Amino acid sequence: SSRPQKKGTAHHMKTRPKKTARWDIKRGPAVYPPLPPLPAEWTIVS
RNA sequence: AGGGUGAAAAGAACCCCCAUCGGGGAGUGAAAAGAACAUGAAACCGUAAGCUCUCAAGCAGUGGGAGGGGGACCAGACCCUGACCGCGUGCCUGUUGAAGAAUGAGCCGGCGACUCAUAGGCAGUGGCUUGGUUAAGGGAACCCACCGGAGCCGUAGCGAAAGCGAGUCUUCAUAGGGCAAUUGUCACUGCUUAUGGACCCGAACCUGGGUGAUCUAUCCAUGACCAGGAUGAAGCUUGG
RNA sequence: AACCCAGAGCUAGCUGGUUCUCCCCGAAAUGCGUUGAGGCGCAGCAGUUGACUGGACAUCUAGGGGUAAAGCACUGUUUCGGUGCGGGCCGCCGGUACCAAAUCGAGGCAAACUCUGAAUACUAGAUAUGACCUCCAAAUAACAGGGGUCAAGGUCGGCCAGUGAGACGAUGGGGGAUAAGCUUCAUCGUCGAGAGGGAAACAGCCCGGAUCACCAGCUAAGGCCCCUAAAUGACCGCUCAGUGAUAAAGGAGGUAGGGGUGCAGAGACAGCCAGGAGGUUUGCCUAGAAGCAGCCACCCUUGAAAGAGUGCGUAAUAGCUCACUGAUCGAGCGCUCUUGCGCCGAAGAUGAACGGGGCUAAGCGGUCUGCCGAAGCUGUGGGAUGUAAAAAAACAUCGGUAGGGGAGCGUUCCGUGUUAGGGAGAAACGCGUGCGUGAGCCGCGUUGGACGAAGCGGAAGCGAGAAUGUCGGCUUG
RNA sequence: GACAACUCUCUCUAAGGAACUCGGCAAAAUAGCCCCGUAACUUCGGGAGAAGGGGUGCCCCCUCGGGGGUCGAAGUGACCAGGCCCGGGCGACUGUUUACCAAAAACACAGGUCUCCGCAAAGUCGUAAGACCAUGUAUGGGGGCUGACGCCUGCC
RNA sequence: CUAUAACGGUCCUAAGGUAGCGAAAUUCCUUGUCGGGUAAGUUCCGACCCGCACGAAAGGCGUAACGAUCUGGGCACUGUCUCGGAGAGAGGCUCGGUGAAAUAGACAUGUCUGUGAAGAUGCGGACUACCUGCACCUGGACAGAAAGACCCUAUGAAGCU
RNA sequence: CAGGUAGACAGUUUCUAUGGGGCGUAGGCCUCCCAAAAGGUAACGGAGGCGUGCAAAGGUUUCCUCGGGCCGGACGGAGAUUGGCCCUCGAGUGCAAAGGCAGAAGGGAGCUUGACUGCAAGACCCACCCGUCGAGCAGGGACGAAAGUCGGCCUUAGUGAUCCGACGGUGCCGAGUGGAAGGGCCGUCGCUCAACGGAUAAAAGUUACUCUAGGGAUAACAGGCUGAUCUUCCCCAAGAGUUCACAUCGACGGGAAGGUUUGGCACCUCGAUGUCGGCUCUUCGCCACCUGGGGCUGUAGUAUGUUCCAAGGGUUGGGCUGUUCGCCCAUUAAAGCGGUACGUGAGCUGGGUUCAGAACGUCGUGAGACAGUUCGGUCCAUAUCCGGUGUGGGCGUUAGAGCAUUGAGAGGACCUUUCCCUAGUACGAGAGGACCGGGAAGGACGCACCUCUGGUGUACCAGUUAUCGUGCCCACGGUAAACGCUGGGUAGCCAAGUGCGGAGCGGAUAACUGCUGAAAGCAUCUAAGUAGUAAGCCCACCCCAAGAUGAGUGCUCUCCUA
RNA sequence: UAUUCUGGUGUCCUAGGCGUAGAGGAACCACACCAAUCCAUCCCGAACUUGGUGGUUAAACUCUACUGCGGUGACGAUACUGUAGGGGAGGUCCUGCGGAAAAAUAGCUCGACGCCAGGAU
Ligand SMILES: [Mg+2]
Ligand SMILES: [Mg+2]
Ligand SMILES: [Mg+2]
Ligand SMILES: [Mg+2]
Ligand SMILES: [Mg+2]
Ligand SMILES: [Mg+2]
Ligand SMILES: [Mg+2]
Ligand SMILES: [Mg+2]
Ligand SMILES: [Mg+2]
Ligand SMILES: [Mg+2]
Ligand SMILES: [Mg+2]
Ligand SMILES: [Mg+2]
Ligand SMILES: [Mg+2]
Ligand SMILES: [Mg+2]
Ligand SMILES: [Mg+2]
Ligand SMILES: [Mg+2]
Ligand SMILES: [Mg+2]
Ligand SMILES: [Mg+2]
Ligand SMILES: [Mg+2]
Ligand SMILES: [Mg+2]
Ligand SMILES: [Mg+2]
Ligand SMILES: [Mg+2]
Ligand SMILES: [Mg+2]
Ligand SMILES: [Mg+2]
Ligand SMILES: [Mg+2]
Ligand SMILES: [Mg+2]
Ligand SMILES: [Mg+2]
Ligand SMILES: [Mg+2]
Ligand SMILES: [Mg+2]
Ligand SMILES: [Mg+2]
Ligand SMILES: [Mg+2]
Ligand SMILES: [Mg+2]
Ligand SMILES: [Mg+2]
Ligand SMILES: [Mg+2]
Ligand SMILES: [Mg+2]
Ligand SMILES: [Mg+2]
Ligand SMILES: [Mg+2]
Ligand SMILES: [Mg+2]
Ligand SMILES: [Mg+2]
Ligand SMILES: [Mg+2]
Ligand SMILES: [Mg+2]
Ligand SMILES: [Mg+2]
Ligand SMILES: [Mg+2]
Ligand SMILES: [Mg+2]
Ligand SMILES: [Mg+2]
Ligand SMILES: [Mg+2]
Ligand SMILES: [Mg+2]
Ligand SMILES: [Mg+2]
Ligand SMILES: [Mg+2]
Ligand SMILES: [Mg+2]
Ligand SMILES: [Mg+2]
Ligand SMILES: [Mg+2]
Ligand SMILES: [Mg+2]
Ligand SMILES: [Mg+2]
Ligand SMILES: [Mg+2]
Ligand SMILES: [Mg+2]
Ligand SMILES: [Mg+2]
Ligand SMILES: [Mg+2]
Ligand SMILES: [Mg+2]
Ligand SMILES: [Mg+2]
Ligand SMILES: [Mg+2]
Ligand SMILES: [Mg+2]
Ligand SMILES: [Mg+2]
Ligand SMILES: [Mg+2]
Ligand SMILES: [Mg+2]
Ligand SMILES: [Mg+2]
Ligand SMILES: [Mg+2]
Ligand SMILES: [Mg+2]
Ligand SMILES: [Mg+2]
Ligand SMILES: [Mg+2]
Ligand SMILES: [Mg+2]
Ligand SMILES: [Mg+2]
Ligand SMILES: [Mg+2]
Ligand SMILES: [Mg+2]
Ligand SMILES: [Mg+2]
Ligand SMILES: [Mg+2]
Ligand SMILES: [Mg+2]
Ligand SMILES: [Mg+2]
Ligand SMILES: [Mg+2]
Ligand SMILES: [Mg+2]
Ligand SMILES: [Mg+2]
Ligand SMILES: [Mg+2]
Ligand SMILES: [Mg+2]
Ligand SMILES: [Mg+2]
Ligand SMILES: [Mg+2]
Ligand SMILES: [Mg+2]
Ligand SMILES: [Mg+2]
Ligand SMILES: [Mg+2]
Ligand SMILES: [Mg+2]
Ligand SMILES: [Mg+2]
Ligand SMILES: [Mg+2]
Ligand SMILES: [Mg+2]
Ligand SMILES: [Mg+2]
Ligand SMILES: [Mg+2]
Ligand SMILES: [Mg+2]
Ligand SMILES: [Mg+2]
Ligand SMILES: [Mg+2]
Ligand SMILES: [Mg+2]
Ligand SMILES: [Mg+2]
Ligand SMILES: [Mg+2]
Ligand SMILES: [Mg+2]
Ligand SMILES: [Mg+2]
Ligand SMILES: [Mg+2]
Ligand SMILES: [Mg+2]
Ligand SMILES: [Mg+2]
Ligand SMILES: [Mg+2]
Ligand SMILES: [Mg+2]
Ligand SMILES: [Mg+2]
Ligand SMILES: [Mg+2]
Ligand SMILES: [Mg+2]
Ligand SMILES: [Mg+2]
Ligand SMILES: [Mg+2]
Ligand SMILES: [Mg+2]
Ligand SMILES: [Mg+2]
Ligand SMILES: [Mg+2]
Ligand SMILES: [Mg+2]
Ligand SMILES: [Mg+2]
Ligand SMILES: [Mg+2]
Ligand SMILES: [Mg+2]
Ligand SMILES: [Mg+2]
Ligand SMILES: [Mg+2]
Ligand SMILES: [Mg+2]
Ligand SMILES: [Mg+2]
Ligand SMILES: [Mg+2]
Ligand SMILES: [Mg+2]
Ligand SMILES: [Mg+2]
Ligand SMILES: [Mg+2]
Ligand SMILES: [Mg+2]
Ligand SMILES: [Mg+2]
Ligand SMILES: [Mg+2]
Ligand SMILES: [Mg+2]
Ligand SMILES: [Mg+2]
Ligand SMILES: [Mg+2]
Ligand SMILES: [Mg+2]
Ligand SMILES: [Mg+2]
Ligand SMILES: [Mg+2]
Ligand SMILES: [Mg+2]
Ligand SMILES: [Mg+2]
Ligand SMILES: [Mg+2]
Ligand SMILES: [Mg+2]
Ligand SMILES: [Mg+2]
Ligand SMILES: [Mg+2]
Ligand SMILES: [Mg+2]
Ligand SMILES: [Mg+2]
Ligand SMILES: [Mg+2]
Ligand SMILES: [Mg+2]
Ligand SMILES: [Mg+2]
Ligand SMILES: [Mg+2]
Ligand SMILES: [Mg+2]
Ligand SMILES: [Mg+2]
Ligand SMILES: [Mg+2]
Ligand SMILES: [Mg+2]
Ligand SMILES: [Mg+2]
Ligand SMILES: [Mg+2]
Ligand SMILES: [Mg+2]
Ligand SMILES: [Mg+2]
Ligand SMILES: [Mg+2]
Ligand SMILES: [Mg+2]
Ligand SMILES: [Mg+2]
Ligand SMILES: [Mg+2]
Ligand SMILES: [Mg+2]
Ligand SMILES: [Mg+2]
Ligand SMILES: [Mg+2]
Ligand SMILES: [Mg+2]
Ligand SMILES: [Mg+2]
């Protein structure tokens, strides 16, 4: 055998998970319409 | 190495277990503090009561908490236990890097290491700045009032030096260049530096002075010892 | 080179150890010199303190250069070609198809070659508000400006540290075997000194830099059959090898596609029927060579077609069969590439060993949308440090080893003090639904039996888990 | 007490007989006494207990060893008590030695040879005084190398 | 005749190894080659000489006797062995009495494989495993008994030349 | 007092990196490359130089152009001197290399001494110490008509801090004062201080007699990484093989795997994590030595050759070695190769770490030394845990028991050689001589066993020696360790003795051989579907076995009294 | 003031150079010829020097023209690369955003600009 193996960090570089697919990279958080302005949390009644 | 019964031996009569020791009562005493006696932590050894483990894999915990128990007054809380699920590669040292199969610690409690003196530098605080300060020494014993200006720091530099001096050395030349044309000090506290063992513990050694020949190495004096058996040199006498 | 004592706490650039808490900042493993290499001096890069400053992050322009690429103008190198002085062999002063400089033509190569020559990098200059609340303009919005606050780089010094064994990864290279988790340099990233998520586990790969609380929310990297959070989602293609965990040359009617080129409707491929002749037994060679041991030639004729013969066969013939042609059959078929995914090549030593179970998708490409996913970001509350000099209110900030700075707690003792308090129970010992960022404090006792706080100050034999420490006590076996 | 494995101190083991093993390590074997016999080799002393063989108890009889009988599987019946032979190296020999991992081929040795020393000697120990050498005197005393006996000991 | 070299030439030294021995306690290559002993011989004996690198008082070559010497072979003999067996004692084992030690971070202390400072009970994935004794066995725990004798360092120590 | 002179004696020194051994080599400076177009930059990376030289090779004024082709010219030739045309920087420049430089920095001529004194703004380089460039100013000059140039050299190497001394100068100091001695200052000289930032003026070895503190920051073994070397293949096919590349070989080259050889690395442990052989004891891999089944053959037969599947079993006994290796003897079916830390040292034992003694050869003056040889030479261990082989208790198994079993799972064993029928039949001209299927005897191994043959048999029985007891004879007893010594021996235990075992027209496969048969109207062992077939795999055989917590099923028994 | 021409003299530059063909003699520049007291040749009045002649555009220089050589040289695209990733056992390949050659060809090129003296218009 004239080929080596992948030890330690080398091996990590090779084997770590990646999304190659151009479509999954370009995804993102959903865009939800804004919320109507909400009331005051707690009010003091005197 | 081995300290502390009580104020006082009042150190426990008498009965019981009973060969003695040891104990349980009674009695002494504020207390038994009962002679292995004063406070009496930890390791370690147990005894009892509450919950719980015998299909289980785990640096023993932690977040969640089934079921069961306990002392409450803010009874929806606290405390003990712990069905099962999740997460969780002892500590130190030292390393590019450790859970390491890298070193170190059996466990528990004590002892155990940047100290002191004196100087130098710097910082922080004061005191004086009619410059600052005293050293040894003297002191109603110490401390301390009051002394003690000898010293020391700051007020002029340049130059090897004579020497000159707000200048001076280098120069034929100030022509240029160099260096100068100003500055507090005495304490206390801290950080560092230096000198002494100088953060602690740890060598093999080095030298000086003694002590050893009852062991062993040689010898010296004077004693003692070596069962039993073989073999048969010289020499000597016999005779060719 | 005895022993004991003394100098002696010898000396040890070496190894081990060096004890309370919280807050802020925070490295280096490089260069030079060294009887130096595991030490040290200075520099580089901490911290704290002052003095000057005006930047940094971006944007554009300008400089010089000789790397990457490229090239043959020089220096080498090199192949063949053209021409050839120059040499070898022969003759007798005669011959040739033999080796060869320079130049030409063609074609290359180069760390120590350059007529050329980038990108970045370096040096320099010039252009441009970092955010947030307010005032605001008849005034609303926005814009403009005033005002206020905050954040942000650098040189020179003072005081005073560590560091001077680095590791891998990306990239450029040298040594080595374009071997090594090897080694040695250069520009960077992470680890060192960095927790969290993804990587089955997994210093150095990817995301992200942890003030703290929350049984809230949105996301990054990465994921969505069950173990195990989210789609047993959607729509296109592919794979049949459990490929989906790894390796090459090479092999191949594997398979799904794409592109050229042959033919054909007077019938193309395969099958089946027949023919496959004459010269001639071609010449040579040979005992023989007759298509078929070997050598050379490989034409011609009759023809629908038939090679002086593709293979078998004979001692040599014969014989079988192929190339090619007519017929039959009636719609595709030939030989070429080339992608994608597979197959074989592919074989080790304790036992599935490639996360498991499993899956023809739960594998692989391509496209669409939901969700999960961290200590990142948001939400709601507390703390601290810097502005900063009381607050309060802002804004920013708060990972951290070596290491530096700030703020504290506790122990014994002294001053106040022959203190307050204490046989109406001190110290100590044991406890706490008490209060602190912690060191700890405050309170309580069916223990204990005589001392002794707080405050405001002072001093140290002042804090222990590590020293094969050390002395006692007690285990384990 | 019991009578496992295994270890150790011991006895025995069919057929074989060193095949074991680094190596016959350890075991087994031999063994006294009397009688016969006894090699190479030699420094003529040895070798030599060479090797190898026979006999052995208890009774009577004869002579002062011999004959006859008789038991036993076995008679020096236990204990005690040599295995031997053929070779080679090294060292002549008996001796000495590393207390506690080495007993030898190392050390010694008789012998050899060199050299110093005439006596108030050389040599050794003492700062010195002096002591040893030696109450000796070159057939003696120091020191160096070699190592019986045999053959020798070459060149520079 | 292949060969070898008594014999010559030259070189250099103070001079160039004579007698005797020789694969040896000396021989590297090397288990030299030959002969013997053995069914088979890296040892042994004899001889060759090509003495890496014998040699003449650091003695050379012989040698009878001697040796708890080193080394080869042979007869006798045997559990040394083929290939183990049985027995006796002292332990081991049970019961009563007395009663240690080295060791020890804490240990609730499986296997395979993978990972990892590159050989894991302790991290991952599977697999296997009721709790706990006793007798035996010694593969592991990088098992235990402190400076690693070997290698390097130290401007260490000592002895010796 | 002086000179000489003994490691007899004393104190000390003996560098760093080599390949972390000897040995010689290297250590400062300069140029080029590496060096990634600023500068800087390492390697035991690749090339070379320097430790000076010139009185002109310096200064200046002024003039000039080298080299290389081709041609002419007495000797004279390839090449000397001379003439001429073409190319234009290819020569030169004291000496390396680099960068420069053509009416020049290159060649010549004339005059010289600036190869000056006093200096110096500012820069570059920079840890420091050093190092480099320099406009400008004054003095006194050289050359030049003058402008101007000149503080050595086209540039970059040609060097050495400090202390100390030496010579020449000097308006300085001069220990009461005057002088002197001696010093200061300026100029300069003196080290291969070359280990070149120089430790002193002055310095080598050795330790296996050794020791201390440390680290393996650095090796020796093993582990890991790597795989050059090694081992096993595959690709191409020049040929060989009567014809014929591919029965069998396969040159020139290529592509791999493995991790067993010799290595590289230094990640690993240094304290007591240690190499090669045997003994005992396993176990696993397959690249298959034999045994089972096949394909091809240049296979007639027997026997081969090569290759495919196959690791269930097997793989002897000796002479020789420290050995891995290897050689032989006699067998054998065959006497396989590897891994497991030499697999195995808290299981055993030899060497090896050649420890201290000694001797030989050799090196060294020497102490001593040797990957030379030789003789001698101490490794301990009561098992805590895991792991194992056995053997119990507890508890579970849903009321408690006693028996009998099913069998998930686990193991043991299924091995092999001759000979004889078949048949001297096929096969072959003969010589030779089968496949297939039957039968016996053996081997090894396993399971038992004691009838026989034995071994032991300290239960016993007999002889017998010495001796002391029982009063003495007789006869017995003790002792001669754990039989005094011998001769026998039953039961037990045991083997060399005796038996027995290895069975399967069961199941499913590997290779291979096949039948029907498409995709490609042909063919094809395969795509559908099936048939044969292996010492292999699984059931059957033999023991264990419901803690098989999934704790099974069956039969029976017992649950009183108040 | 212009313009044209000759000679001198510079600066800028794309470095204007060689070749072929043509033009210039009144002026200007040059050679040609002749003689050597200043000076001159390592030999030579060749060069350099002083003083004459009056010949010629032959050489030289000058001016116009021309791509044959020479010099210069794109646009595009490609190689390379900065940064953000991806593939491969590796040697090395690929993508996005930004920069961007060398070579080769297409073209360009027979310089530009200024002062002085001297003629001519
Ligand atoms: Mg490999
Ligand atoms: Mg991984
Ligand atoms: Mg995403
Ligand atoms: Mg009483
Ligand atoms: Mg009594
Ligand atoms: Mg009493
Ligand atoms: Mg009472
Ligand atoms: Mg009372
Ligand atoms: Mg008490
Ligand atoms: Mg279970
Ligand atoms: Mg458990
Ligand atoms: Mg470590
Ligand atoms: Mg370490
Ligand atoms: Mg301790
Ligand atoms: Mg320990
Ligand atoms: Mg203390
Ligand atoms: Mg200190
Ligand atoms: Mg002090
Ligand atoms: Mg005495
Ligand atoms: Mg005495
Ligand atoms: Mg005595
Ligand atoms: Mg006497
Ligand atoms: Mg006596
Ligand atoms: Mg006697
Ligand atoms: Mg001593
Ligand atoms: Mg001390
Ligand atoms: Mg002292
Ligand atoms: Mg010292
Ligand atoms: Mg910070
Ligand atoms: Mg050091
Ligand atoms: Mg700083
Ligand atoms: Mg440029
Ligand atoms: Mg260039
Ligand atoms: Mg290039
Ligand atoms: Mg190129
Ligand atoms: Mg060229
Ligand atoms: Mg060309
Ligand atoms: Mg280059
Ligand atoms: Mg150019
Ligand atoms: Mg250009
Ligand atoms: Mg840029
Ligand atoms: Mg350094
Ligand atoms: Mg280093
Ligand atoms: Mg790296
Ligand atoms: Mg490069
Ligand atoms: Mg290569
Ligand atoms: Mg560190
Ligand atoms: Mg970081
Ligand atoms: Mg990051
Ligand atoms: Mg943040
Ligand atoms: Mg933060
Ligand atoms: Mg979401
Ligand atoms: Mg789910
Ligand atoms: Mg789906
Ligand atoms: Mg797979
Ligand atoms: Mg035929
Ligand atoms: Mg899976
Ligand atoms: Mg969160
Ligand atoms: Mg947090
Ligand atoms: Mg938080
Ligand atoms: Mg945050
Ligand atoms: Mg605050
Ligand atoms: Mg604040
Ligand atoms: Mg404040
Ligand atoms: Mg912090
Ligand atoms: Mg710190
Ligand atoms: Mg107190
Ligand atoms: Mg007190
Ligand atoms: Mg308190
Ligand atoms: Mg009282
Ligand atoms: Mg103290
Ligand atoms: Mg105990
Ligand atoms: Mg017994
Ligand atoms: Mg006996
Ligand atoms: Mg026997
Ligand atoms: Mg016999
Ligand atoms: Mg013996
Ligand atoms: Mg015996
Ligand atoms: Mg006899
Ligand atoms: Mg004899
Ligand atoms: Mg011998
Ligand atoms: Mg002797
Ligand atoms: Mg001894
Ligand atoms: Mg002896
Ligand atoms: Mg001796
Ligand atoms: Mg005398
Ligand atoms: Mg001797
Ligand atoms: Mg021999
Ligand atoms: Mg040998
Ligand atoms: Mg032998
Ligand atoms: Mg020799
Ligand atoms: Mg001699
Ligand atoms: Mg003899
Ligand atoms: Mg003796
Ligand atoms: Mg037995
Ligand atoms: Mg006993
Ligand atoms: Mg357990
Ligand atoms: Mg690994
Ligand atoms: Mg493992
Ligand atoms: Mg765990
Ligand atoms: Mg064990
Ligand atoms: Mg044992
Ligand atoms: Mg462990
Ligand atoms: Mg040193
Ligand atoms: Mg020293
Ligand atoms: Mg000495
Ligand atoms: Mg650069
Ligand atoms: Mg550079
Ligand atoms: Mg270098
Ligand atoms: Mg000159
Ligand atoms: Mg001037
Ligand atoms: Mg010159
Ligand atoms: Mg000096
Ligand atoms: Mg005087
Ligand atoms: Mg005077
Ligand atoms: Mg005086
Ligand atoms: Mg005087
Ligand atoms: Mg001067
Ligand atoms: Mg030095
Ligand atoms: Mg130096
Ligand atoms: Mg010196
Ligand atoms: Mg020795
Ligand atoms: Mg010593
Ligand atoms: Mg290991
Ligand atoms: Mg082939
Ligand atoms: Mg290391
Ligand atoms: Mg150990
Ligand atoms: Mg196979
Ligand atoms: Mg045949
Ligand atoms: Mg097999
Ligand atoms: Mg097997
Ligand atoms: Mg086998
Ligand atoms: Mg057979
Ligand atoms: Mg072995
Ligand atoms: Mg072991
Ligand atoms: Mg010698
Ligand atoms: Mg011995
Ligand atoms: Mg146990
Ligand atoms: Mg039950
Ligand atoms: Mg049964
Ligand atoms: Mg079954
Ligand atoms: Mg089971
Ligand atoms: Mg069977
Ligand atoms: Mg027949
Ligand atoms: Mg048969
Ligand atoms: Mg029997
Ligand atoms: Mg019987
Ligand atoms: Mg018997
Ligand atoms: Mg009697
Ligand atoms: Mg008796
Ligand atoms: Mg089948
Ligand atoms: Mg077939
Ligand atoms: Mg068909
Ligand atoms: Mg099928
Ligand atoms: Mg079968
Ligand atoms: Mg049951
Ligand atoms: Mg159940
Ligand atoms: Mg141009
Ligand atoms: Mg132009
Ligand atoms: Mg003309
Ligand atoms: Mg042109
Ligand atoms: Mg372009
Ligand atoms: Mg990239
Ligand atoms: Mg350009
Ligand atoms: Mg171009």
Image (cartoon, coloured by chain):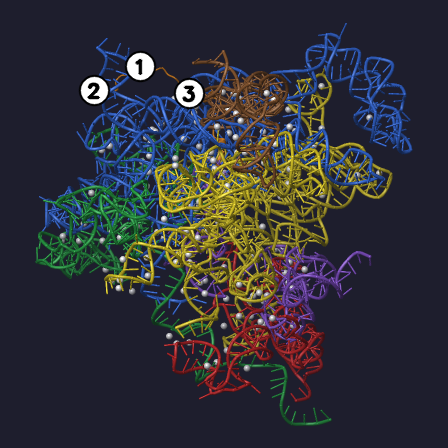
Chain colours: A orange, B green, C blue, D red, E purple, F yellow, G brown
The crowding category of the residue bearing disc 2, from other C-alpha atoms within 10 Å (few below 14, some 14 to 19, many at least 20), is few
Q: Which residue is mark 2?
A: A44
Q: Report whether residue A4 is seen.
A: no
Whether the residue under disc 3 has CB within 8 Å of ligand 3: yes
Q: Is residue D103 left or right of residue B144?
A: right
Q: Tell me the quarter of the picture where residue C154 sits.
A: top left
Name which of mark 1 and mark 2 comes first in the sequence. 1
Q: Amino acid at mark 3?
A: Gly
Q: In this figure, which residue is indicated by the disc labeled 3?
A: A28
Q: Residue at x 31, y 14 (%)?
A: A36
Q: Residue at x 27, y 16 (%)?
A: A39
Which numbered tag is attached to residue A36?
Answer: 1
Q: Are marks 3 and 1 on the same chain?
A: yes
Give the residue displayed 38% in from the left and 17% down from the top: A31
Query: How many circles with numbers are drawn on the protein?
Result: 3
D127 or C29: nearer the viewer:
D127
Where's residue C326, x and y in %? 80, 11
- Of residue C75 and residue C198, the one placed in the foreground of this image is C75
Tag in front: 1 or 2: 1
| Mark 3 element type | loop
Q: Are marks 1 and 2 on the same chain?
A: yes
